[PDB]
Image (spheres, coloured by chain):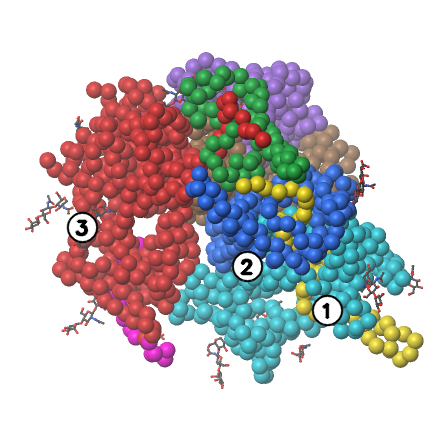
Chain colours: A brown, B red, C cyan, D yellow, E blue, F green, G purple
Amino acid sequence: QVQLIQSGPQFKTPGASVTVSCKASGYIFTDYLIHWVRLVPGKGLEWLGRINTNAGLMYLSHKFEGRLILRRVVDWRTPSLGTVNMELRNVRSDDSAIYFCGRVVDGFNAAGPLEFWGQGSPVIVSSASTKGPSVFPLAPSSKSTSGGTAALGCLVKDYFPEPVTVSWNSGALTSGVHTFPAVLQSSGLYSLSSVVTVPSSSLGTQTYICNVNHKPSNTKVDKKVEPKS
Amino acid sequence: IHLENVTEEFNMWKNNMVEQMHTDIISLWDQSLKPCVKLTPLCVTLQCTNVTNNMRGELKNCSFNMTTELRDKKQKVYSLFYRLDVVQINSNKEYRLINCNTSACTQACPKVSFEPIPIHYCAPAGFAILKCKDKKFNGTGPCPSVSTVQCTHGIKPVVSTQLLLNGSLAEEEVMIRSENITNNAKNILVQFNTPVQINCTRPNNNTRKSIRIGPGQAFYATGDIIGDIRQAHCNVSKATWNETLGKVVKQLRKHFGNNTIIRFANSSGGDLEVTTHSFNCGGEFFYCNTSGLFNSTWISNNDSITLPCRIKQIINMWQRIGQCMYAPPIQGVIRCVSNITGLILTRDGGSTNSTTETFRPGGGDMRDNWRSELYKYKVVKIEPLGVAPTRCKRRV
Amino acid sequence: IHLENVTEEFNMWKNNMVEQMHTDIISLWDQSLKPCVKLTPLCVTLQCTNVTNNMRGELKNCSFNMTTELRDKKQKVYSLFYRLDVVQINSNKEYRLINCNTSACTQACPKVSFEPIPIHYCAPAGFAILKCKDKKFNGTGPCPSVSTVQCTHGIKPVVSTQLLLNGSLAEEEVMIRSENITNNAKNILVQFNTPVQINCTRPNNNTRKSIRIGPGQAFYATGDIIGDIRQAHCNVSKATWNETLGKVVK
Amino acid sequence: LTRDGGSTNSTTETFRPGGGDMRDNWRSELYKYKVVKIEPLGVAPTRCKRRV
Amino acid sequence: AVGIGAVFLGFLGAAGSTMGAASMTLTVQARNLLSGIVQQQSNLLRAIEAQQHLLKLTVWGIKQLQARVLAVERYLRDQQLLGIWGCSGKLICCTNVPWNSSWSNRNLSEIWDNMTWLQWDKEISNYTQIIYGLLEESQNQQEKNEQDLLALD
Amino acid sequence: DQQLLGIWGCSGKLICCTNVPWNSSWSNRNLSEIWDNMTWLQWDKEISNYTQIIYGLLEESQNQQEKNEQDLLALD
Amino acid sequence: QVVMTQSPATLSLSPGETAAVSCRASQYVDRSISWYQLKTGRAPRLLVYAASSRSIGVPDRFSGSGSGRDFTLTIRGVQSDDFALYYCQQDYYWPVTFGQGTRLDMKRTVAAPSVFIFPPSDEQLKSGTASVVCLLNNFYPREAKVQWKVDNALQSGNSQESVTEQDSKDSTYSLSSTLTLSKADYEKHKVYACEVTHQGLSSPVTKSFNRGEC
Ligand SMILES: *[C@@H]1O[C@H](CO)[C@@H](O[C@@H]2O[C@H](CO)[C@@H](O[C@@H]3O[C@H](CO[C@H]4O[C@H](CO)[C@@H](O)[C@H](O)[C@@H]4O)[C@@H](O)[C@H](O[C@H]4O[C@H](CO)[C@@H](O)[C@H](O)[C@@H]4O[C@H]4O[C@H](CO)[C@@H](O)[C@H](O)[C@@H]4O)[C@@H]3O)[C@H](O)[C@H]2NC(C)=O)[C@H](O)[C@H]1NC(C)=O
Ligand SMILES: *[C@@H]1O[C@H](CO)[C@@H](O[C@@H]2O[C@H](CO)[C@@H](O[C@@H]3O[C@H](CO)[C@@H](O)[C@H](O)[C@@H]3O)[C@H](O)[C@H]2NC(C)=O)[C@H](O)[C@H]1NC(C)=O
Ligand SMILES: *[C@@H]1O[C@H](CO)[C@@H](O[C@@H]2O[C@H](CO)[C@@H](O[C@@H]3O[C@H](CO)[C@@H](O)[C@H](O)[C@@H]3O)[C@H](O)[C@H]2NC(C)=O)[C@H](O)[C@H]1NC(C)=O
Ligand SMILES: *[C@@H]1O[C@H](CO)[C@@H](O[C@@H]2O[C@H](CO)[C@@H](O[C@@H]3O[C@H](CO)[C@@H](O)[C@H](O)[C@@H]3O)[C@H](O)[C@H]2NC(C)=O)[C@H](O)[C@H]1NC(C)=O
Ligand SMILES: *[C@@H]1O[C@H](CO)[C@@H](O[C@@H]2O[C@H](CO)[C@@H](O[C@@H]3O[C@H](CO)[C@@H](O)[C@H](O)[C@@H]3O)[C@H](O)[C@H]2NC(C)=O)[C@H](O)[C@H]1NC(C)=O
Ligand SMILES: *[C@@H]1O[C@H](CO)[C@@H](O[C@@H]2O[C@H](CO)[C@@H](O[C@@H]3O[C@H](CO)[C@@H](O)[C@H](O)[C@@H]3O)[C@H](O)[C@H]2NC(C)=O)[C@H](O)[C@H]1NC(C)=O
Ligand SMILES: *[C@@H]1O[C@H](CO)[C@@H](O[C@@H]2O[C@H](CO)[C@@H](O[C@@H]3O[C@H](CO)[C@@H](O)[C@H](O)[C@@H]3O)[C@H](O)[C@H]2NC(C)=O)[C@H](O)[C@H]1NC(C)=O
Ligand SMILES: *[C@@H]1O[C@H](CO)[C@@H](O[C@@H]2O[C@H](CO)[C@@H](O[C@@H]3O[C@H](CO)[C@@H](O)[C@H](O)[C@@H]3O)[C@H](O)[C@H]2NC(C)=O)[C@H](O)[C@H]1NC(C)=O
Ligand SMILES: *[C@@H]1O[C@H](CO)[C@@H](O[C@@H]2O[C@H](CO)[C@@H](O[C@@H]3O[C@H](CO)[C@@H](O)[C@H](O)[C@@H]3O)[C@H](O)[C@H]2NC(C)=O)[C@H](O)[C@H]1NC(C)=O
Ligand SMILES: *[C@@H]1O[C@H](CO)[C@@H](O[C@@H]2O[C@H](CO)[C@@H](O[C@@H]3O[C@H](CO)[C@@H](O)[C@H](O)[C@@H]3O)[C@H](O)[C@H]2NC(C)=O)[C@H](O)[C@H]1NC(C)=O
Ligand SMILES: *[C@@H]1O[C@H](CO)[C@@H](O[C@@H]2O[C@H](CO)[C@@H](O[C@@H]3O[C@H](CO)[C@@H](O)[C@H](O)[C@@H]3O)[C@H](O)[C@H]2NC(C)=O)[C@H](O)[C@H]1NC(C)=O
Ligand SMILES: *[C@@H]1O[C@H](CO)[C@@H](O[C@@H]2O[C@H](CO)[C@@H](O[C@@H]3O[C@H](CO)[C@@H](O)[C@H](O)[C@@H]3O)[C@H](O)[C@H]2NC(C)=O)[C@H](O)[C@H]1NC(C)=O
Ligand SMILES: *[C@@H]1O[C@H](CO)[C@@H](O[C@@H]2O[C@H](CO)[C@@H](O[C@@H]3O[C@H](CO)[C@@H](O)[C@H](O)[C@@H]3O)[C@H](O)[C@H]2NC(C)=O)[C@H](O)[C@H]1NC(C)=O
Ligand SMILES: *[C@@H]1O[C@H](CO)[C@@H](O[C@@H]2O[C@H](CO)[C@@H](O[C@@H]3O[C@H](CO)[C@@H](O)[C@H](O)[C@@H]3O)[C@H](O)[C@H]2NC(C)=O)[C@H](O)[C@H]1NC(C)=O
Ligand SMILES: *[C@@H]1O[C@H](CO)[C@@H](O)[C@H](O)[C@H]1NC(C)=O
Ligand SMILES: *[C@@H]1O[C@H](CO)[C@@H](O)[C@H](O)[C@H]1NC(C)=O
Ligand SMILES: *[C@@H]1O[C@H](CO)[C@@H](O)[C@H](O)[C@H]1NC(C)=O
Ligand SMILES: *[C@@H]1O[C@H](CO)[C@@H](O)[C@H](O)[C@H]1NC(C)=O
């Protein structure tokens, strides 16, 4: 059994210093190099550095020198247990990523094949503060535009942090629903261009309510719609 | 007694008695602190400012309220501390001692010297120690010449991080040992053919002052410095250091494939006690940044290096989180004159296609200081009964 | 090993090893407390009021002054206590802890559990334990079938008053035994033929809070009770309990 | 259980849940063990004699 | 389980068998009287191992060490007491003290063929401190008689 | 050790001859090479297979010998 | 630093077909390529830890291979959870580097997008801002784009685009595109269009309005 446990998700403001911890268990913790790998969303992975859990020394990707520190905590008693802490100093909004703790393959302490991984800690960096969405109807796109499918939606807009939750008719409508994955805009706030598609027999006569909620603010809103011009 | 005609397998990595020695030193250390004064009244809010009469921003001058022997009476009093002893708890800045959120501290009693005496470990009756005699023995394998002895050499319990000193020297050549070498998580221990000699000093003329905390309890403030203040530092002869590394490199080439670019670098990253060479000199704990020593590269072909130091009054040995202890400021000026015996290296993976041989001063637990001296010993149990056939019978 | 043809007098009342168990358990208990924090600074004057979010009057909510780690600094702080932990020292009512006139107290360390592990008692060399094997043995008389053994059962050191639980039970019948029965000042020990199974609960969603008493010393305050406050209680089946008394009466 | 004397008449058996020192919780589990010291020496007569 | 000859391969298993048949098993009690200390020296352990601080619970091990010194010493006293009777090499001795049948009237058959050792104990425990006195003196003079013989030759 | 060396009927001595015959399945080696070639440390590594057999045979060989002597004294 | 190229950008396969994903290094690296499967919301999973050395606990349908400069992860009988991202990773020189990754996509027949547009909501206009939204729905393959036009002259940098996970029912995807302006910038113009580009279409389907109508 080998097991790595990280800290939960975090929000940080620009210029702050962010700490991610990683508890390590089930094997002789001094005898494998731990590595840190960063998953920037949509992009490929990026490698931060590795730490010699015995000697305590660190080795870093040149790009991160001075701006990054890695540390190790251990006891000579209970060698099956230990910890690594990553401190990324002076964060930017473009440091927004998942930070993964990882460990090398057995007998392979000179390279980067990682066998065991922590659950990954999201670190999102913005100047924003807790705010529920505005709800704007994408009121059904009319027969003078849409043809045989009534496309409609709700532009659930300008909120932070995630998550919002969205449904149509409080979940009684699911056919053709697409809660498009949210974009963290240039404003530092999320937006979610949600839609539902239904037959143009039923443009607004059959019920369409977007049901909206935002657990960080605990804000809750709803909105009915009918066809545009 | 030299055991005629013998040959048997030693192993210093799986050797139990290093663990006994490690465990004993901790126990003897604790009892040497046990009767001394617990400093809890000093965990109090300090007004502070920098020292005046001087580069060094390192000395804080601090004033606070302290108990007298009389429970109802307390006194305004002041002392100096190093910047590493204090945290800004906060106009002037305002402070606490570093330990004061996590433990009390014991002040070490002035009468007890720290200095490491020789210790002998002895075999209990019905057991024998064996000693490997072969001067070319690495840390493992069939030693081809052995002696028994009832008790060891006079091993001295020095404590040090990045390099080891006043310890025993191999006679033949520079020796290097590891539990595997190739696996980077293992240390490489290095032991020298000849010592290389270090001078260290703390040139500030210290005046100690006594504060009476309570009815029979005293605390030893840093009272004043007389004359100018100047940095604690250590020196080594550059020629003899350069010679010594020339010899360690010529050994490492045997394992690392001859024509490979071996090089040294400083102890990258983390906190002060992994990044520095740290040792006690006569009652002061030094922390010195060895990058002046470990900064060189080696293709297959009269003056002193100086390295500066920082000092702490509180220390926390063997990373034991609850066990602060406070070392009183020792009087006057001090210096140490010591033999560097050998050093601890850690390897890094292939830096490029060309080299797999960046080395850095290592560390870990203090335990492999004992594994440096206990490298040739083993312990065995006599099994005196035996049965064998011959041609005699008992009669009835 | 069964000691064939053997038969000899056992007496469980005059037995020495019960007194060694009693003395061991007390000593093992004390040393489990000895490394832990002495709670002395909590013996201080308390301002108090009844709890709000509830029948019970059993919980008091109390506020007091306590030292920080820094000797010269102290804080207003508050916690919940039971009406049995506090005494009125006396406008609002004013209190102290119950013990605070007669002794200090040690806080039990959270990492140490009170759960009872099995313990075996073993004979030193040149002595033997004997075990009476007879399933109708009453604790006093010539046992007609015995074994030696080097070391006992896994005895578990539970502690309880009026009735005793998770211990071992005889296979033949309900056993009842006493040093004399007829003399009222002697107990009767009753051992059942079968268990009867108890469920017990504390239905409060309890919240711990940590207070630093000093430099590295902390006290675990009762912080808050979320949801409804409700009584701790135990259940046992009326049918099998009534049946079990029906057997001890016989 | 603990007993009481004749409660008015007929019954001598109002039983009540008892107690005491915790010691008899151990006497519940240790109800069947005993400890003995071995005496390994013995002397007994038979028809055999040693010679000088 | 229950009977003569069966359980003799275990410690004390003979104890209800009659004295004649029990006389074969004497080595088993003799060995287990001391070497049962394996259940002590295999498992007595101190600080760091299983325990950290609580220091009176390391020094609680005085109970276990005190039992060991009593065990070796009580055994060693038998080897002294068996030795001065001129008998230390053996599990059995014939000796030149005559049986005074005042100590028991019971004939040679019924003692070996009927009684168990636990039954015989309860008779001779009246007289044993006479018998040990006679055995000591019977050897004490025999040592001297032998020294005179080795001399007068 | 002194107990174990005692019950084989051997307590007073550094050396004993004893009445157990050597089964050469315990080692096929001849009487010269065992005394003249090997060290005691080499011999241990063979007989450590069979030692618990040989101790059992020594014990029983003595345990009956005590009784045969008691009868030889009893036939007076 | 070592650059890793993968190809293709995405591999499209039916359940039970066989896969071949290429990776290549900017200079020689000696057999020292790992391959990671990445499933969304979970840590990457190690398939191969040097060329052909399969990880313990990995099913034998995966097999790596390669030289000193180019490499190939191979899968036999692609399964319902093999549709994921795959990254090759290099570590012969520090720092460790990774390719851009390859998506594995469940093959299905060509399907053109259905297409829709919305002007900004009346409440959004009254709030002082204007998002013009365009929906492209249930197309296959994944390759789709919006071109945003204002006064029906083509424009750039004024929009964001979001795309669904792969539809498990029918392999399709949907794209939601959003042009956004201040209400003044929205009312400084008079015409709007979203033009749709997709792998299968006859011509770029364009949905449009004059400002204030759909
Ligand atoms: C002393 O210390 C050393 C260093 O730690 C240690 O050596 C290491 O031994 C391990 C043993 O596992 C070597 O690990 C790899 O083993 C697999 C075997 O795969 C099969 O079996 C496993 C069983 O678990 C299955 O998982 C798997 O599916 C297979 O069925 C090999 O495939 C690996 O191959 C690499 O090493 C070969 C050389 O041994 C190379 O030819 C090959 O290219 C592979 O990559 C190496 O070469 C690259 C190019 O030069 C280089 O850049 C890479 O970094 C890599 O070195 C592999 O053998 C492991 O290789 C050993 N470590 C090193 C650094 O080589 C000793 O075991 C230890 N000894 C003692 C007594 O403690
Ligand atoms: C550290 O801080 C302390 C406390 O502020 C300083 O100690 C005080 O220093 C002043 C002068 O700077 C002393 O006052 C002078 O004393 C002489 C005594 O002969 C007298 O002639 C002068 O008229 C004047 O009074 C003062 O006595 C001294 N002590 C206290 C308790 O205030 C100290 O200077 C700082 N620096 C160092 C290196 O300690
Ligand atoms: C040593 O002990 C003394 C006495 O306890 C401490 O001196 C006192 O410190 C306080 C807090 O800084 C001072 O209070 C201030 O007083 C002014 C004027 O009343 C008020 O405007 C401020 O808001 C503040 O309350 C107080 O004047 C001062 N002196 C006395 C006699 O109380 C001292 O801080 C302790 N430490 C040291 C290093 O001396
Ligand atoms: C210390 O010196 C001894 C020799 O005195 C070194 O012993 C060497 O140990 C290695 C294994 O660690 C041996 O390698 C193995 O050899 C067998 C040959 O049958 C082969 O089958 C295995 O694949 C493996 O190669 C090696 O033979 C042995 N001898 C020598 C001269 O190297 C010991 O390793 C040295 N310690 C260190 C830390 O190097
Ligand atoms: C460690 O190495 C350094 C450098 O070799 C040694 O420093 C030298 O120490 C002497 C004695 O203090 C200095 O002489 C004095 O210099 C001052 C300022 O120039 C002058 O006012 C005095 O009259 C006297 O000449 C010497 O300048 C200094 N050398 C250099 C180049 O800094 C140090 O002594 C060594 N010792 C130890 C114990 O580490
Ligand atoms: C190991 O050796 C390296 C190289 O000798 C050390 O790196 C140096 O670290 C110092 C920290 O004081 C850096 O100094 C600073 O420079 C920047 C401006 O570049 C300034 O903003 C800082 O305030 C500070 O003054 C220095 O740049 C850096 N590199 C060099 C060429 O010196 C490293 O500190 C050594 N580590 C240890 C623990 O010995
Ligand atoms: C390594 O070995 C050196 C050399 O022994 C240690 O340094 C010092 O050695 C000298 C001579 O043994 C000590 O001198 C003595 O000092 C006392 C107290 O002042 C005095 O009464 C004696 O007459 C004699 O002069 C000296 O104290 C000691 N230096 C210190 C400050 O400890 C060194 O301690 C050893 N350990 C290390 C880690 O270097
Ligand atoms: C011991 O550790 C220090 C870092 O803690 C090592 O790095 C040295 O740090 C200093 C201060 O940051 C560097 O100072 C230089 O100052 C000039 C001022 O004009 C500036 O132009 C430079 O950019 C730099 O900041 C110093 O350069 C740096 N050392 C090196 C080798 O560059 C220090 O080296 C360590 N001690 C020894 C004896 O190596
Ligand atoms: C650590 O090793 C590096 C090389 O790996 C050393 O590099 C350079 O060495 C020189 C002489 O030690 C340094 O001093 C300066 O050199 C220039 C040469 O033009 C001279 O004009 C200056 O007056 C001064 O002597 C130089 O700063 C240094 N440069 C760099 C980039 O490190 C380095 O000195 C070594 N450091 C130590 C503390 O061993
Ligand atoms: C036990 O007694 C304590 C202390 O009297 C009570 O704690 C205090 O309760 C009040 C409300 O009755 C809290 O004030 C509220 O705080 C929130 C913070 O978000 C604020 O939104 C409200 O407007 C209001 O100010 C107060 O924070 C709390 N703590 C203290 C130190 O006063 C407690 O209610 C009593 N009962 C229990 C079950 O603890
Ligand atoms: C926590 O510590 C604070 C500060 O020591 C305590 O607050 C103070 O308590 C005293 C005693 O009840 C109050 O004294 C009364 O003041 C009024 C007005 O001056 C006067 O009419 C009364 O005769 C009496 O002297 C005092 O006002 C109060 N506040 C302050 C700022 O001192 C507090 O009692 C402690 N305990 C708790 C649970 O907070
Ligand atoms: C536990 O069970 C044993 C039998 O296994 C009971 O033994 C009985 O003990 C009583 C005294 O407690 C004996 O009574 C005495 O009998 C003689 C007969 O000669 C008479 O003269 C005395 O006056 C007295 O009555 C009784 O004989 C003995 N045996 C039997 C079979 O009852 C023991 O009493 C039980 N203990 C309890 C508390 O149940
Ligand atoms: C011990 O015995 C008591 C009585 O049999 C058990 O209490 C009963 O527990 C159930 C389940 O929690 C209660 O049902 C729930 O009641 C609430 C309020 O009416 C309702 O909102 C829920 O939907 C559900 O029906 C039941 O009311 C309660 N009965 C009584 C009379 O209190 C208890 O659970 C037993 N077990 C334990 C471990 O104590
Ligand atoms: C329980 O112990 C008793 C003695 O206390 C055993 O009873 C009988 O003991 C006699 C000797 O006193 C045995 O007699 C001999 O038996 C053999 C074989 O039958 C025969 O060859 C001899 O001539 C002589 O008669 C007798 O065997 C023995 N058993 C019986 C059933 O009488 C008794 O053996 C022990 N219990 C058990 C279950 O073994
Ligand atoms: C030295 O003192 C000045 C004035 O009190 C202060 O601003 C400065 O921060 C101090 N130096 C350091 C290293 O903090
Ligand atoms: C001294 O250092 C220089 C530079 O590293 C090197 O050329 C020289 O060979 C060294 N001395 C010896 C004896 O190797
Ligand atoms: C409950 O509160 C009232 C008013 O504070 C008090 O008089 C009463 O005694 C309290 N009840 C109990 C049981 O403490
Ligand atoms: C159950 O209790 C009732 C009243 O005490 C009693 O009549 C009945 O006999 C009991 N059950 C049994 C099986 O005795």
Q: What is the three-letter code of the residue carrying label 3?
A: Arg
From the top left corner, tell me how far across and down residue D7 is, in percent.
87, 78
Label 1: chain? D
Instruction: Give left or right: position of B359 versus B207.
Output: right
Mark 1 residue crowding within 10 angstroms, few (<14) / some (14–19) / many (20+): some
Label 3: chain? B
Which quadrant of the view contains residue B135? top left
Please give the label number shown on residue D19. Answer: 1
From the top left corner, tell me how far across and down residue G70 is, in percent.
46, 15
Front-most of residues E125 and B228: E125
Residue at left offset 70%, top offset 68%: C54
Residue interval drawn in magenta: B69-89
Instruction: Give left or right: position of B8 versus A82.
Output: left
Q: CA distance from mark 1 to mark 3?
A: 72 Å
Instruction: Give left or right: position of C153 versus B282.
Output: right
Furthest residue to the bottom?
C90
Mark 3 residue crowding within 10 angstroms, few (<14) / some (14–19) / many (20+): some
Mark 2 residue crowding within 10 angstroms, few (<14) / some (14–19) / many (20+): some
Instruction: State the residue position of label 3.
Output: B335
Query: Can residue F9 be spotted in the picture?
Result: yes
Q: Quadrant of ligand 10?
A: bottom right
Instruction: Provide the secondary structure element on which disc 1 rests.
Output: loop
Mark 1 and 3 residues: CB-CB less than 8 Å, in contact? no
